[PDB]
Image (tube, rainbow over the protein chains, first blue to last red):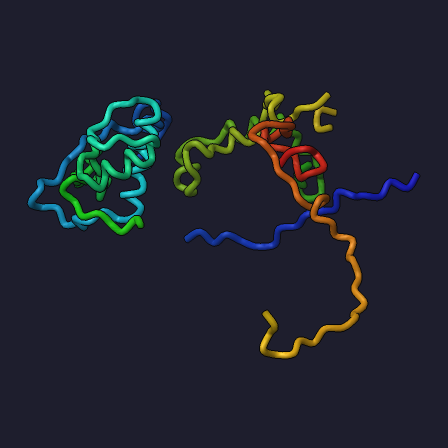
Length: 129
Length: 64
Length: 50
């Protein structure tokens, strides 16, 4: 009985050189749950990130708005359009998009999330064309 | 399988015996040897293995 | 319109290689056979999905 089509064999050859008494409490250790964070919004005069939307952020805004226009139907465009993509794009260009860009720069160990909330209607818009 | 040699006298370190020996170990030894408290040597002997969910063994070969 | 340059035209022996586009081309829809283990589509054209 020639079987053939063997499952081979697999070999790993390397080493991972990853460079007060105590007992078992259940509350001092463990706690897989992470502490709830508090949102610190950096004041509008202390924001040091770009006031021009990146192509990534502008694309994300347009995509989110287009999806929400696919589920909803409300908009502020005087010129009506037949596609949610067009409506969202013109909403971004006309500076009437109902979305905010939150840029997170910190995770403080005290459970503090420091963010900069940027208004796309006041921001510069990249090429996108 | 493990083999315990006492100056030429050998006796098989069966998993139950190893389990008792590891249960004899305190947390201070584990911590002071760097191992995490969740990595206590007692956990290395299993009396109730996990039968994996049928999601990872579908079709009715590992089930054999 | 005649070409300005004289064009080199003559018989050349040509072979049809047995790589048909109709065999190679494949298109799949949004649904079909899936792998029981990973839940992903099956592999390739032969399995009618992937």
